[PDB]
Length: 296
Length: 258
Ligand SMILES: Cc1nc2c(s1)-c1nc(/N=C3\C=C([N+](=O)[O-])C=CC3)ncc1CC2
Image (cartoon, rainbow over all chains, first blue to last red; front, side):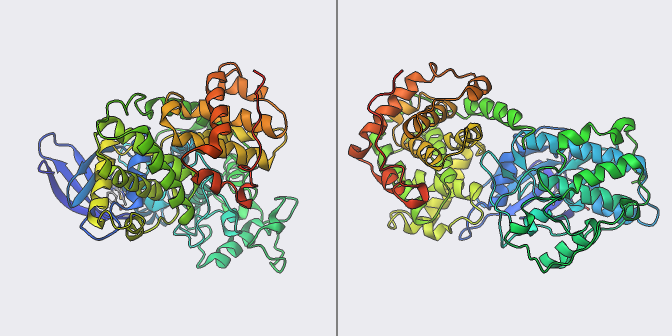
């Protein structure tokens, strides 16, 4: 820690405060995530245990690079590579003007490559949201904050007292299924994709029932035909309203046909029919993907 | 619906080779023995049952212990402190909400303090270089189950039972990789219950001929026969419950016909 100089605070994660810092010896600018580890608590928090272990297995351009873990008596520091800012800020700053389509398509392509890498190395992220996605001045976007990430060598069980986002939560989780799957991450990335295009959150719910009704009123109320088993799920009720699927052209106007085809395959109700990250990368939407740079 | 099961099974086969405990590590331990390890591992089974923990949490804790005991010398009075620390870390990694540290101290009959357990946790992390996502027999067995034709609850619960028994005895089962034990376990459950064998689907996927599984299938058979006489009984008692379809009451085959 002697070699690092704290420049400024850049944020707060799922366990500690984060600073921008520079290596006095090499010059490299980093992001120092500091967790206080006094005496009496529960020890090293589980969020830290998972982020460190999973993240040091994952080496990929579209996943934040954990550079070093500095280990002391009363504090634990995680040294990450520094990125310029997060998506949420870039969205708010690019609100009204809009994020250019080519930069949207580049970003989703890169996010899908990172997600395909995670899933093939049995890692669920579970918390994909604009605040957790980081961008730099060169046009890269990277998956970050793996505190709630789980290894799914054995199926990952559902929380109930949750602790996740909402907004970017998959419908099968809201309807009470027992297990997570890689489909919940693709649902989140679909919502973010729609959000960059419409410049606003797709399903901004205030509770679980409020969140379901926001999905329902945009994609229609699911039945046995689109999603067999859906009427025999714990949190499903036959009193739910019977709404109809709206035309995708009125939900994401500024999107071409290839784009709407993709978004609709990412927001498929049935987790089995929902498109995988690997499959999405082969989609015609990404046939003309370029690498533009943001106005940052 | 898969798409990367093959990628995952490939990657788990890479990782188990790297996350493997040193095979002859107990000979180089001055104060501790395989029999002491058997008591520790068995106590952890009872801790799992008492605290309603996942069967995977158990498998990961044993892996942590075996890796930690591969590079650090430990005296008998501290072996339980290593195991408690291992279980606390496996609980933080695999459980949604792990038991509090206060609970992990109470299970030790106040042999250790909260301070010591918190300190061991930190030492365990340092020795293992924060590599906690280790492949387990339990993991491979879950994948192998997808190649059942058809599914059988007794086969699944029996396979698990035999997989947990291998955790108690380092004396043979540290020379086999988790995937191989999982294979032996899977065949022997299949054979005892329905008379079926280690399927063709898994021979092509894993590359393990029934003949390659034979050495391990022999040791596990004896263990299954000798189980009711073993010094350690926590796993048999655990798998007598109706939630595991009473698979431990079942009669082992007298021969295997290999
Ligand atoms: C909770 C968090 N985890 C990380 C964060 S934030 C992180 N952020 C950044 N970059 C910045 C992020 C922001 N921001 O608005 O979150 C602002 C300036 C820089 N750069 C690197 C990281 C590393 C991982």
